[PDB]
Length: 354
Image (cartoon, rainbow, N blue to C red; front, top):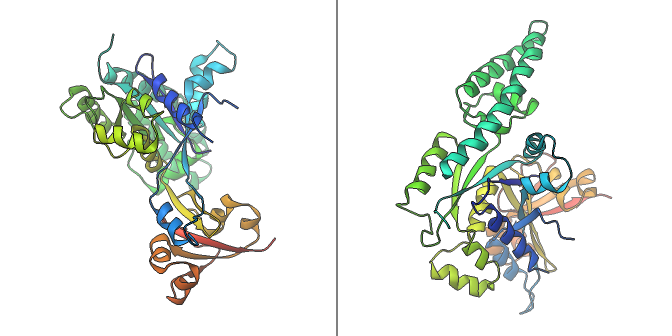
């Protein structure tokens, strides 16, 4: 489960935020109070829908989503008291990226929370290397091919000592294998979510705090996404066309959550590929780099182990052509093998065995 962990200290709105996210899921077709999914909007999905509308009846479209998790909620829930700090770190370790909610409008310091949560991860990570190096600094004098990771491990270790996060360490073949071998919380991507007075939407310009943030975020390698748990509390209920308006109202073309959900998507370096027919259109998600059969994996598993090949064509072409058959006459549906690297937008039909 690639998922974004929302985390935030009290009275910042983290509660309204996650709450709508659920509320939306909620106003929709077992209450996992701390787990929610923001459906992603994908225009391509409808273009594909027309292309297979046989008449005026059309087929259903299923979008893909981004999973969001409430770190604390999850930590509370189960039952400890001892080492709440560690249970936190245990989950924060289980998610691909961290979405920290920062408040940027007084109510009845966001840069400071930004520092608390970071410094914690920074400390935890330090133990993680101090301890890895003990072992790895020694493995290194027996086996030489473990020597490139020492460098990496060393460099990384000084870096954190300087307050600096893993995520901002210069990439190298070396490093990368090291991080996979020893996952560092500060290596995960960070999305500083700025909660603002909705009179500040779309990006709360000329609002020093939300501007303060933008400047930390740049020093920390985090992206920034602005929103109003509040507006996000309203939109929660309005109907698409009615949310359409309210969004129109403050003139935003995307819900604050959506904003965050794609920022999520980027952070997890994710990408899309759909299956499209007369009976259904659908967006599937995979991490860039995934190969044609692991992709078939998602839809179903018999598809990956029985994978013979995949017919593939970009959603635009398939659309420009009117359907499968014609796309083939235009000679545009490629036949791809076991190691074809699925591409964003790609449309796939898999020829598998059993």
